[PDB]
Length: 377
Ligand code: HEM
Ligand SMILES: C[C@]12CC[C@H]3[C@@H](CCC4=CC(=O)CC[C@@]43C)[C@@H]1CC[C@@H]2O
Image (tube, rainbow, N blue to C red; front, side, top):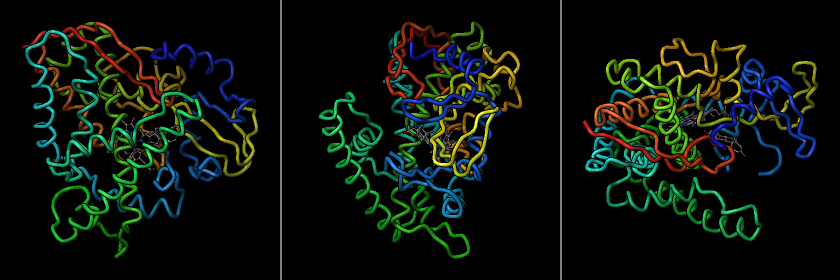
C-alpha cells in the first residue's frame, strides 16, 4: 500500500541511488550521504524555484542572503525558553482534545486527535480569538487542501476556492498584525512584531506569508508525525507499555518516529552549478528530489535501520532536514508530539490497531484514518 514505500526505497538505494526520471527530467537521491549533501550543500543545491511558479513567498523557496535575514528574525519566536512558556498551554489543549474521546472503546486517531491538535495549537499560539477559531480552521483546511484529481476542470475549481481562502486568511492575518501592534501579547504575531536584528524587522509583506507557512509546514507534518509514531509504537509489541512505564524515553521515541516514518518523505532542491553524485553528473537547473524517508532507512547510516528502536540516542536522522533550512518548527513539533503521546499513554492502558487508510497525499507520508481499539485507564 502507499503506507509501505520502504521496499521501494531499499530497491532504489541498491539499484539506482542517483536516478534520472527521463519523463519529468528530474533527479532522485536515496542514499543517506547523498540526501544529506543535496539538502545541505547550499552552494551546489538551491531552494529557489525557477519556473512552475504552493511555496513561493515563503523562506522555504529562498536562498542567502535573503533567506538568512528572515530566518534570523523568525528564529526569535521559537527559542527554548519560548517553548517552555507554550508547554503548559499545549498540555491543556491536548487534555481537552483527548478528553472528548472518553466513553468509547474505538477511536479514529486522525479525526479525533492527530488532525485537530496542530491546528488548535498553532491557532492558540497565533493569538486567534476563540470567536474566530471555527472560521480559522476552515481557512487552514483550504490552505493545506489538494484537488480531487489531476483533471484540469477539478484543478481549476479547487484553485478558485483555495485562492479565495488564501486571500481571506492573508487579510485576516493583515488585520491581526495591525491590532497586535497597539495591543502586544505573548502570541507569535506579537513576538514577530517586536523581533529585531539591529533595527531590521519583518514587514507586513513578509509577516503574512510566514504566518501562512506555519500552517502549511506544521499542520499535516505534526498530524502525520503523531499518527505515524503511534502506529510504529503499536507495531512493535511491548513498546506502548515501555513508554508508559518510563515516560522520559518519549522524546527519543519521537526522534525515532521521525527517522522510522518521516511525515515529510522528500525535500526539493534545484542544481545551482554543475556537479556530480556517485559517478553521475547533474547539470545546473535540473530538479533534485532528496528522499529523507529513504535516507533515514539507509543501512549504511543506521544499524538495523528497518527496526523501530526507541533507545537510539543520539539519533542522526535527517527527517527535519539538514543545514540552513533545518525545520524552524522542530522544537514545536517535538514538544507537541511529546505532549500528545504523554496524554495517550496516560488516558489509555492499552491500544490496538483496528484498521488504517493511507493519506492520499503524494508528497506526504501519513494516515487518513487510524481506527483504534482502546481501553481507558
Ligand atoms: C511535525 C514534523 C515536521 C517535520 C518532519 C518537518 C520537516 C521539515 C523539513 C524537512 C524542512 C526543511 C525544508 C527544506 O530544507 O527545504 C522543514 C522546514 C520548515 N518547517 Fe517543518 N516539519 C515539521 C513540522 C513543522 C512545524 C510544526 C512548523 C511550524 C510550527 C514547521 C515550520 C517549518 C518552516 C517555517 C520551515 C522552513 C525552514 C526554512 O526554510 O528555513 N515545520 N520542515
Ligand atoms: C517538506 C515540506 C512538505 C513537502 C514540500 C516541501 C517543499 C517542496 C515541495 C515541493 C512540492 O511540489 C511538493 C511538496 C514539497 C516536497 C515542504 C517544505 C516544508 C514542508 O514540511
